[PDB]
Image (cartoon, rainbow, N blue to C red; front, side):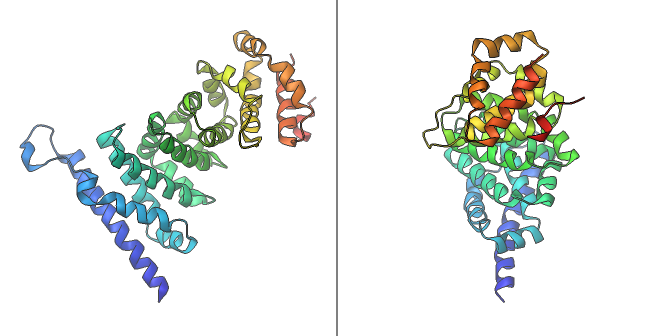
Amino acid sequence: DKRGRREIRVLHLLEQIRAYCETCWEWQEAHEPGMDQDKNPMPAPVEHQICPAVCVLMKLSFDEEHRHAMNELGGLQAIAELLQVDCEMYGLTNDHYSITLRRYAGMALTNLTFGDVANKATLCSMKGCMRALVAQLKSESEDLQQVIASVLRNLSWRADVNSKKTLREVGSVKALMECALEVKKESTLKSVLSALWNLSAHCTENKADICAVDGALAFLVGTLTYRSQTNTLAIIESGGGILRNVSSLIATNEDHRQILRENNCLQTLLQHLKSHSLTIVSNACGTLWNLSADMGAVSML
């Protein structure tokens, strides 16, 4: 009864975005740039009332039963393909319609990937979408950046081998670190640093990429003494978590050490040892140990 009602409702919405996607794919894949322009104008989302469809799916995605219906009909892939094709068609634009459409799609994807092994793997297997998502981090819209960081945060958490490789390949590390440097809102920084913390533990390359970004290390040391206006330790914990993960690389690079030194990192880490947060204490111990130039006691804290 009501289940069929939910499925039909969700199905109609997905058929709508799919039909639009098929029109965009045909245009992008078969339309020869120079050939009777008037008979094949580039599709526009607004002309097909697409955002409203994505808005409904985004709202319904907060309800578990509707998420189940979406998962039975390949809803995540459909939404992802739409986000991807729109980004490829219009790139980075300051268009209010396009920004909202992408934010609604990203929010649905965050809801659909939350604690869903299958959906996370599926989204990461879509490398074109992944490149599109990462590109959105350069958007002037901080609300969009936050949505994308949240998607990347879910994907970087407990990622399988394939997902980890994709996340690295599309350059999400550099993109996230560069984004962290320009964000103005704390809520945004939290999602960005949280994602970077997950990513910084995947492999050595990710660690090297973080350190390579100009101003990154100085910025990370700065998060150690961050004064959260919302009275939280989230920034200090994630920023310090990232620092701990890349500290092993910093240890063998005098230039980087010099940067931590100039920013009085050591003194701050020693102060962190007194924290009421086990995460902060643990991060500090790990950083101090790595920088301090058989086994250590790190893996026991």
